Amino acid sequence: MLKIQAYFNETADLPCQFANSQNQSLSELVVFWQDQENLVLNEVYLGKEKFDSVHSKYMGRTSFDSDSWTLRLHNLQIKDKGLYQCIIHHKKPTGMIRIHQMNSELSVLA
Image (tube, rainbow, N blue to C red; front, side):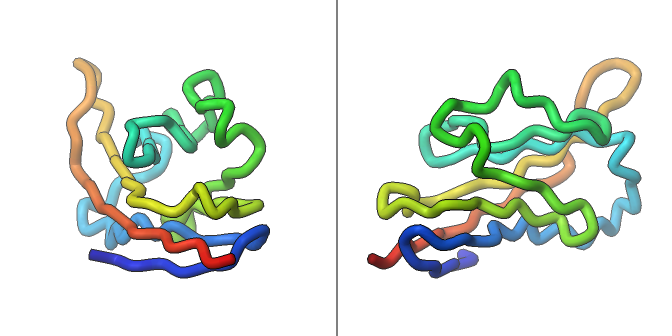
């Protein structure tokens, strides 16, 4: 289990741990990040960020980097500690197929 540690009011990079052996391009994928309570942190629909699914709890605090397949969670709260998940779908003309998953344990120290 990937364990991350950051401090209160600081920042954290939640790793998606996607080698991309599938060699997909972002324009063909749908990337989601949700917390232990299945709340959306960030969503990148076929390459474009979609904020109408993001929970207010995260509005303005996330930023996804495709180069590293990492979501950056800003302005950490002691309440942000917990388990997070990266979920990547390959959107086929039909619908979607899940091709990846990873969890990260974020510890926020005061």
